[PDB]
Amino acid sequence: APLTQDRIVVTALGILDAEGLDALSMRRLAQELKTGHASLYAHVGNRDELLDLVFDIVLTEVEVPEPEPGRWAEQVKEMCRSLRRMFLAHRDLARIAIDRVPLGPNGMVGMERTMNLLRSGGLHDELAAYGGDLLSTFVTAEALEQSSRGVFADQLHGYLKSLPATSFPNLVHLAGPITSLDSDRRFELGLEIIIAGLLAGAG
Amino acid sequence: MAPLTQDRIVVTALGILDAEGLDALSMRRLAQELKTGHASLYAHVGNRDELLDLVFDIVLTEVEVPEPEPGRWAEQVKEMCRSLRRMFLAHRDLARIAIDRVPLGPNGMVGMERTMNLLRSGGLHDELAAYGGDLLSTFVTAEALEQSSRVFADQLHGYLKSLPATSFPNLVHLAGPITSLDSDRRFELGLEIIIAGLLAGA
Ligand SMILES: CC1=C2C(=O)c3c(O)cccc3C=C2C[C@@H](CC(=O)O)O1
Ligand SMILES: CC1=C2C(=O)c3c(O)cccc3C=C2C[C@@H](CC(=O)O)O1
Ligand SMILES: CC1=C2C(=O)c3c(O)cccc3C=C2C[C@@H](CC(=O)O)O1
Image (cartoon, rainbow over all chains, first blue to last red; front, side, top):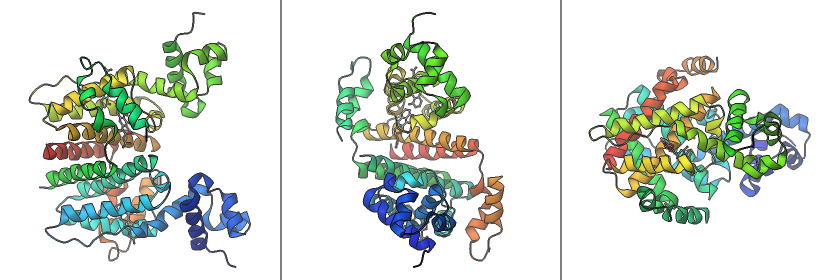
């Protein structure tokens, strides 16, 4: 004994890290916990519900600095890199998250902290409220593409290079970047773009 | 009956999509609708996965990428995005389909060519132009998805608003903005942020 929600969640996360999402069935989980379905459902509900809890549990891995003046740009980037670290350390997690609710204790307080750091930058509400949404969406998407990946890049990269340079001039000349941009490079590139935009729209 | 063509196949599939949604689109359902055998259907379009690439590419014709007019770069970029957004909103389950798919194709590639042309015409260096295009279309697709997904806002707004203001000042103060910002308001904010940043990087 005995089944707790937190104990169920750590177990489901344990097997997600090891063997990935599709190997996370309620049956497998129930099997690991050596318990009956009934007790499992009562605690975490169904699989969507379980994922939700798993998503929230790993959010503690994300660190949101307290705002230092002079340092907003860099601090927001820290937060974002922290979120990406979480995604990279957890198989299939970005897949769990890009759909679902940070509406849970850990996500709720992480929001508060995130909103605090954003507003401190002189962003205004709509801008702060949305910016946080934008950054989160950005990081999650970039992380989904990362874990997604090979040679596709290479077959695609070459496919574009072969284009009739007379009709598809830009494509041939941009074939490289389009296809095979360093993951870290894309992240940092997108990070700067969004951050500069937020500042531009603050003042 | 007239000999099956790829385009008639694909138009019909889009019709089922639009009316009935992604999950009602099967090769069996499409065969029914077309009154043809599974061989001639497959001959033309392959499996469901391939069918979807074709459906996606055919709708891209609805998107308009202006030829660069000097003076108006920033606004023409927003124009292109609004048009791409329009297409998603006009088409059910589409943003979902686009989420794992390379536009590449007749219009797909043509519109990328035209997009990179607009981007670089703004003084964006190869790498900003290329990524900016990716970031821009990823942003539009994600907003579309979101918009389609959608009382809940009032429930969430109620919860955030009724929080201990001493514990969650920001979540209580930003209760509304967070809960719901029309899809239009979100979209434009997101556009101006990204376009301003592309300009800063250039
Ligand atoms: C859940 C959570 C966070 C977030 O959800 C988060 C985010 O969604 C987007 C961008 C940044 C963050 C940061 C955090 C930090 C985290 C801290 C905690 O709950 O202990 O709490
Ligand atoms: C391929 C294509 C387009 C695009 O791909 C596109 C885009 O990717 C992002 C934002 C806007 C657009 C617009 C178009 C328009 C269209 C080009 C054409 O075939 O005429 O078809
Ligand atoms: C969602 C997505 C893309 C697109 O959807 C896209 C598009 O819809 C029309 C024209 C071009 C594109 C390009 C992309 C690139 C990529 C972005 C990402 O997943 O980060 O994955």
